[PDB]
Image (spheres, coloured by chain):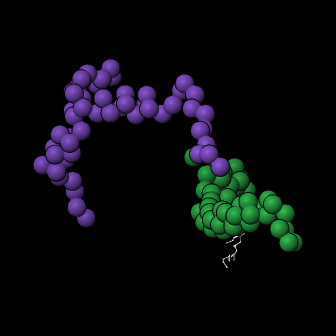
Amino acid sequence: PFTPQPAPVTGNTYRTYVNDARTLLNSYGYTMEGKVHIPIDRAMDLIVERGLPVR
Amino acid sequence: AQIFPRNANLLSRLSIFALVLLVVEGILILGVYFRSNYFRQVNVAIEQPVAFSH
């Protein structure tokens, strides 16, 4: 029993979406409808600084 | 010469040699069978009831 060699996947995969979104999540930028992006981990730091209502 | 042919000498020596080879071969077959992929079900794609593909 030789180790199987599965056929490779097709052209279209999830990697393009994830890579594009991960590139978008940082490096600032300008969204079409709004004004400005904020890198991930910077918006999260801003969320802790301003905080959220409790109870 | 009394009760045996001339080639009995070679036949007896070859029989001893073949017996040793057969013992070694039996040991080897036993070990290989117990270390085989069929025995341990390795590299065999087990068919599933719903045919899920990772």
Left or right: where does residue B42 sit relative to residue B12? Answer: left
Left or right: where does residue B37 sit relative to residue A47? Answer: right
Instruction: Specify the quadrant that holds the N terminus of chain B.
Output: bottom right
Which of these two is toward me, A16 or B35?
Answer: B35
Left or right: where does residue B12 sit relative to residue B24? Answer: right
In the picture as drawn, the residue positioned furthest to the front comes out as B2
In the picture as drawn, the residue positioned furthest to the left comes out as A49
Left or right: where does residue B20 sit relative to residue A14? Answer: right
Quarter occupied by residue A10: top right
The answer to whether residue B22 is visible is: no
Residue B28 percent location from the top left of the image: 62, 63
Which of these two is toward me, A29 or A16?
Answer: A16
Q: Colour of chain B?
A: green
The answer to whether residue A24 is visible is: yes
Q: Residue at x 22, y 27 (%)?
A: A27
Which of these two is toward me, A27 or B34?
Answer: B34
Q: Is residue B50 above or below residue A35?
A: below
Q: Is residue B35 above or below residue A4?
A: below
Q: Residue at x 67, y 63 (%)?
A: B17
Which chain comes out purple in the rendered image?
A: A
Residue B32 percent location from the top left of the image: 62, 61
Which of these two is toward me, B46 or B9?
Answer: B9
